[PDB]
Image (cartoon, coloured by chain):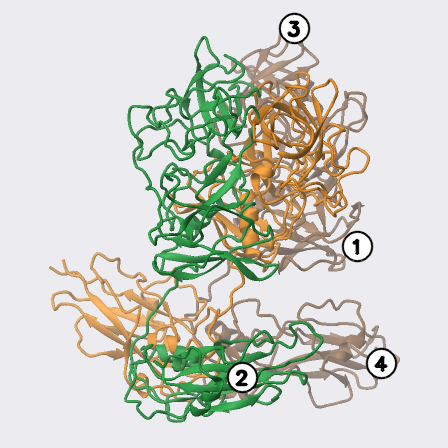
Chain colours: A orange, B green, C brown
Amino acid sequence: NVIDPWIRNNFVQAPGGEFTVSPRNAPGEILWSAPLGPDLNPYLSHLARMYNGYAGGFEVQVILAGNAFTAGKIIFAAVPPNFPTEGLSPSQVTMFPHIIVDVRQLEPVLIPLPDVRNNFYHYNQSNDSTIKLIAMLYTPLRANVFTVSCRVLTRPSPDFDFIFLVPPTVESRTKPFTVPILTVEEMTNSRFPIPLEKLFTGPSGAFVVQPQNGRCTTDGVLLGTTQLSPVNICTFRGDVTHIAGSRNYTMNLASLNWNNYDPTEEIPAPLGTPDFVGKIQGVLTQTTKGDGSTRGHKATVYTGSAPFTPKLGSVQFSTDTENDFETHQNTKFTPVGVIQDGSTTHRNEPQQWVLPSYSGRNVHNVHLAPAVAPTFPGEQLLFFRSTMPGCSGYPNMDLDCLLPQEWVQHFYQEAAPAQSDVALLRFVNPDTGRVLFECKLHKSGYVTVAHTGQHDLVIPPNGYFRFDSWVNQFYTLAPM
Amino acid sequence: NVIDPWIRNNFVQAPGGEFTVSPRNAPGEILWSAPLGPDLNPYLSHLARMYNGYAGGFEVQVILAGNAFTAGKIIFAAVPPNFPTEGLSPSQVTMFPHIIVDVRQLEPVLIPLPDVRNNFYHYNQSNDSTIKLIAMLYTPLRANNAGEDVFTVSCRVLTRPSPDFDFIFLVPPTVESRTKPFTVPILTVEEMTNSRFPIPLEKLFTGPSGAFVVQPQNGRCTTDGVLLGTTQLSPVNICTFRGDVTHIAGSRNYTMNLASLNWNNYDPTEEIPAPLGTPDFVGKIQGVLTQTTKGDGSTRGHKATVYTGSAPFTPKLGSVQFSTDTENDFETHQNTKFTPVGVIQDGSTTHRNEPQQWVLPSYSGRNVHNVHLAPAVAPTFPGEQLLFFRSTMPGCSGYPNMDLDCLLPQEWVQHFYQEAAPAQSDVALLRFVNPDTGRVLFECKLHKSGYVTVAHTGQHDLVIPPNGYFRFDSWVNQFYTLAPM
Amino acid sequence: NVIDPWIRNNFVQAPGGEFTVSPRNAPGEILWSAPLGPDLNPYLSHLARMYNGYAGGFEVQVILAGNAFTAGKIIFAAVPPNFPTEGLSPSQVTMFPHIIVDVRQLEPVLIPLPDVRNNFYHYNQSNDSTIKLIAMLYTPLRANNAGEDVFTVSCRVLTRPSPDFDFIFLVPPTVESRTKPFTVPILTVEEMTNSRFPIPLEKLFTGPSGAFVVQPQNGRCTTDGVLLGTTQLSPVNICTFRGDVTHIAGSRNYTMNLASLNWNNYDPTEEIPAPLGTPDFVGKIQGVLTQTTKGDGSTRGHKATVYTGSAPFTPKLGSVQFSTDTENDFETHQNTKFTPVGVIQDGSTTHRNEPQQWVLPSYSGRNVHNVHLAPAVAPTFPGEQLLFFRSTMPGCSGYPNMDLDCLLPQEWVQHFYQEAAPAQSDVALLRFVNPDTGRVLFECKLHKSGYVTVAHTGQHDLVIPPNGYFRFDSWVNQFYTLAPM
């Protein structure tokens, strides 16, 4: 019902009150825009943060500063709010309500600002005003260096007041979806502990894309065979059993902490098992439980083998030795590099798109996180291209994963429920400050781009990713 | 005069006044404090910061919520602010201005709060100010019912401006942007990885700082995210080797011009002790060396051995020897890659000897000392003991020194790089709240220099509940003494 | 305040009404539709073209003239702003605020409407659509007499604004024009020709989008005329080839040094998938190869069998193979031209196979695929089916896959090339109108990329009156669906 009288009677300076008027400026051009309203008188603006709507007008004032040597004329006026002001002559400006000024004046000058007391509640969250103030170079002001300066002074109308008492805005904010500021060269693969080297796009029809390492909710519930620690992907911990004469070892599996694994849970597998058929030379490693004598020897795992049964609790490893790893020790498979010890096929393995035998070839992998494809058509998925090492043979080392492993943990620390389906995430290279590409990250937990064909996405390795907002499910990217 | 009447004729929830009581509570002890002032109302806070002049008093309403079974009578009062209130008898709190409330009072009541009438224009910011508020239980609260921790009574505080309230002086306000809240990851220590070797940690350790000379170079960064030491961000790049081997024509060894994470050629001309991810202590470790042919991609694998105490190990110069079980399979100038997993104890009679974690390697060989040292660590506030992360590396042939005590968690480094937080004082306060019990098992003392300690004596493998998150609280000074566990 | 007294005091006509009712009727029938607004009164349409701000209401006022002894009634009503009203129920009209009126009243009748206002403004330079007009027949008004359809009962509208109505904002007039008003050709399917083969079109088709990989390269252009794909202007330039054949002296083949439509020598370095007029499918086709010697005109012509699924078909590289029926007749380095007539089926022993109308051929060969791909189409607001243009290509050998579906009408592409129209919203609205009755069989959903869908399901060769044409209407959003067939 009342504000400070000292606020009401006198004027005040505004954050837009500045002008660099040179003859080097082009005549007939816009040089200051500002939406009129509460957002202009500063002490009034903070005092009006808490109140949620308006009834009244304002009066503005102008104060100029130049020399007696130049001669210029300058206009101020008011517009419709949504009115395009871009293609606009300085001639036709004066048809709007307006006041022209000279270059050589002393007193402050007010503007009419014609009023229709709307008596509605201009909501402070919204972006709409009555007008947008304007200024334009009317006479080009040549002389014989000098630059002219002008400032904006302001107060509200006497018949202005407020509406309601409201608590400070944004007191509580939903996790604001802090995307990590990393690069994909810094981030690692979600299907193997290896740093991602390139970014790939392509069709989902070329494969069946349903892995189980790299599956989680956007708000942090444990999904698939995805777990937390990246090094626990495709390593093994359990209790090997000696085959009598062969190089094999069937291993009664355990946990990360060598705890007794429970096969009776609602899980696809032990958390950290590979989700693909593959042959890989690694190193099975064992120490004595009595003193701690370490030993590590080159081993080969077969996730397309029938004794590989993690959901049952046995897994086969073909080592270079035959009886070095004792039974029921701390025996632990460390993968090194995928080999191609199968015929002469080029890039046959790991079979990254088929599912392995968790419960064996008798019972399929249970409790499976589903597959994905661009359901919004015209777009292609975002694959994270890798290339695994190898010591002997040339297998298909191109590993395309879907998530960053650190992003799973980071968004677990978020544990954020979404605000729409599709987010607005932008790869900004801060060397440029420019977006190379945007994307369509879905609140299920996967991402798509409207780009054509197969492309290894050549990007500056200093570039980060910049999330913006929550888009509806009906937007199509422009192609690159 | 200057406030709208919806403030001047109502009440408002406290900004922080929130406290419970308990049958485990005891009479005489304190419950809840507050400095009275205009800071106790959010509306008056925001409509005060834009002003400077200040006068008047307040009123305080209060409200409880209690059942009929629990019996108790409660007490609030006023006090002059410098008064020491430590072990006051509840009966002497009679003499202050005060009111008694029964706990089963269903309706709100109001504190009297007599004004001192020594107003004379307080300076509107001074914490050295008038009356504090005191929360206290008068009665023993026998509270007898068959429930467990039951009828834990909630309590709320309300404020109100007095009728003789005002402001006096006008001023443009401040912007006051905000900083970082010093968040830490909430994992278990056994889930986080070692930062001087790519392995997950196992357990938390403490021990005397005079036992070892502790200065590694992997796991060295600021508390606001500027790259230090030989420390990089990707944990698989630690202790691995990548580059182009050239065949020594007779032995199982090669000379390898070192390569990056993404096989970029190593630059010896940077302000670094070593390449990023170099093994920062002397050891013998048997992982595996692989090589991908640059023509087709024939994946080969042969188990290797690296020797960080060897003279041909020269990371800063650009050649390190590797002794694989094969002699010359790894072809000329290809992408050859060593990945370590576990340490063996071979070629050395000494048992439980390698790796030697508290020495520094030969980065520029045995010729030039390691330059640009991120410095060693020792407790400034004496008597305390440093916090290690003890784990166990795999051991295949022999009995090596598998005791690996690193100084930092690797995920914390990237966490803090995304934080990039400027400190508020020197040493932080982190708690191990086990969320199963919701209670502390131990604390720490985390410096802004980038290391952490605890005031506990002797060697201690800290056995924690594996469901335990970690709870940062606040900023301690350089003179706080922890309690021993 | 802003307006003249006289224009507000009395009622003034409206140009859209004035319409007559013959006694031969069927009740429950809509007669006349109109959008309410200030563009009703020509006075007010001028004055609102002058101004910006728009607030208040009207009074619609109706006078009848004709017979009296009919005993037949009329309804005027409100409506939802997007409401189909063709064959619907009059009970719906009874739900809205409406008025029943018989012809026996001498006083002119007025229908009241919903009374609201939005006091900030209403745009007035937009759609700004509101309650449209309802001319609804209640009782079929038989006019029992000796005459046949005598005293055709006229119905006028003669309005004036409500006394609260007024303007607020004024703009420069800028009365001039809109953009291109998105004019359409009025052709039929026999008059329009195929945009992927030089043949006249036969029938439009609707069918499921999941059937084939729907991505051609002939028949691709924007809604404002930028060259996309291998699409060019002339319909006869499609699938025909020009250049300098080279003697494959042992076989019927001829590799052609590629020349353009104007016989300009081909540049293989342009930002194109293929040359202009090049096909975008795999199929075998017999047409006729023709060659005229540049010196005097020693003419020759023989039937050539072409394969865009062949290895020497490399239009982006600059060579293309033609297997004629003759072997050494066509001289080298002459102006040699192939023209097709219809796809054949020499075949792989499979009938109705070629052209594989949805696959892409070897533009730069099989090794590197095509570049600058105009993308595929998809129903973005789904449940709706695409628009195909079902045709039948001729043949010279076998049983070819004659069902030819193209994407755009070739006349409409060059029509838009003349238009160069910028879009106003997402989806335009085109109506296939039978001008024999002036009524629409089906509508469409044209997307601003340059494709169009319809909201129906199933395999339908759409039956059309061969006198039927197409008539553009408006701009609909991307979430309204059409009525199925």
Mark with earlier residue (2, 1): 2
For the residues carrying marks 2 and 4, which lies nearer the camera in this image?
Answer: 2
User: Which residue in the structure is indicated by mark 1?
Assistant: C485
Is C53 left, or right, of B24 in this rendering? left
Give how far across and how far down residue A91 sits, in percent: 32, 66
- The reply to whether callout 4 and callout 3 are in contact (CB within 8 Å) is no
User: Which residue in the structure is indicated by mark 3?
Assistant: C250
Question: Whole-Å distance between the Cαs marked 2 and 3?
Answer: 89 Å
Q: Which mark is residue B94?
A: none
The subunit letter for the residue under badge 1 reads C
Question: Whole-Å distance between the Cαs marked 2 and 4?
Answer: 41 Å
> Is disc 1 placed on a helix, strand or loop?
loop
The N terminus of chain A is located in which quarter?
Answer: bottom left
> Is disc 2 placed on a helix, strand or loop?
loop
For the residues carrying marks 4 and 1, which lies nearer the camera in this image?
Answer: 1
The subunit letter for the residue under badge 4 reads C
- The reply to whether callout 4 and callout 1 are in contact (CB within 8 Å) is no
Q: Do labels 2 and 3 share a chain?
A: yes
Q: Which mark is residue C165?
A: 2
Say which of C124 and C180 sits in front: C124
User: Which residue in the structure is indicated by mark 4?
Assistant: C143
Question: Whole-Å distance between the Cαs marked 4 and 3?
Answer: 90 Å
* Three-letter amino acid code of the residue under disc 2: Phe
Report which quarter residue A112 is drawn in. bottom left
- The reply to whether callout 2 and callout 1 are in contact (CB within 8 Å) is no
Mark 3, Cα crowd under 10 Å, few <14 / some 14-19 / many 20+, is few
